[PDB]
Amino acid sequence: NTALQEVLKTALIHDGLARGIREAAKALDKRQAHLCVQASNCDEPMYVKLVEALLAEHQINLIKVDDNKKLGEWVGLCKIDREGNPRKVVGCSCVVVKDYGKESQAKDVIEEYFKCKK
RNA sequence: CGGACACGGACAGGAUUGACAGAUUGAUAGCUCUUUCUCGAUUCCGUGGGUGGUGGUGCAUGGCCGUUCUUAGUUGGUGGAG
Ligand SMILES: [Zn+2]
């Protein structure tokens, strides 16, 4: 439970992402992105087959989560506030990590890759 | 758009920029249109809003200048006249 809860959220503050309706699946076209994350609630079953057709054949792995509404408070557009509303953004299916830039808590995402998923 | 900012919706399962071809036009303005890529949450729309103005009004004014006015005039205080 260490991989999905805490070691990746620190790699989501100010990195390079794929954010919105004209770029949810734009950053998959980049040969510059490391370990990404993917949501298991797509409306059509081939759009996730569309995006794993990039990564899983290649050197890139996805992490499953539930959906792109629990992912909304992670992507960067803050919707919840002291004087705010609960749901003013609906997040992406798949945001990628192109560069960590530092090594605070990144030893477990790379341990997530080649411990059992090899 | 060079209409800041504030309000909600449209913004991640397809908001907003740009652009070659061509019948497009005054025009190598992608203006529009057919076709179709790119840009990355910056925005666009709705509503209140500043804003800019060689737009009005010099009879609402400030500054300035012009003039009788380049001729020798103007004024209190303090007493006196009323
Ligand atoms: Zn008029």
Image: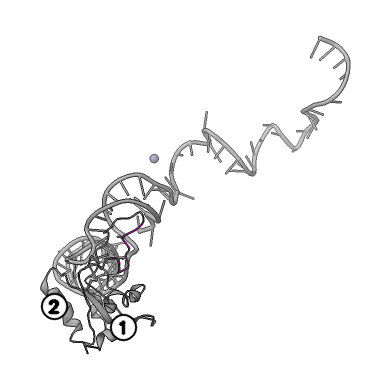
Cβ atoms at labels 1 and 2 below 8 Å apart = no
Measured Cα–Cα span from mark 1 to mark 2: 26 Å
> Residue at left 27%, top 62%?
A89
Q: Which of B73 and B72 is in front in this view?
A: B73
Q: Mark 2 points at which residue?
A: A49
In the depicted view, which residue is nearer to us: B4 or B7? B7
Closer to the eye: label 1 or 2: 1
- Give percent across and percent down for residue B14: 19, 65
As for residue A25 lying within the magenta part, the answer is no
Placement of A62 over or under A89, stated as above or below: below
Say what amino acid the circle numbered 1 marks. Answer: Asp
B76 above or below A102? above
Determine crowd level at label 2: few under 14, some 14-19, many 20+ residues with C-alpha closer than 10 A: few
Which quadrant is home to the N terminus of chain A? bottom left
| Residue pointed to by mark 1 | A108
Which quadrant of the view contains residue B81? top right
Element at badge 1? loop
Q: Inspect the image, locate mark 2, and give the three-letter code of the amino acid beneath it.
A: Lys
Segment tinted magenta in the rendering: A73-82
User: In the rendered image, which quarter is residue B5 located in?
Assistant: bottom left
**Is most of the magenta stretch helix, strand or loop?**
loop
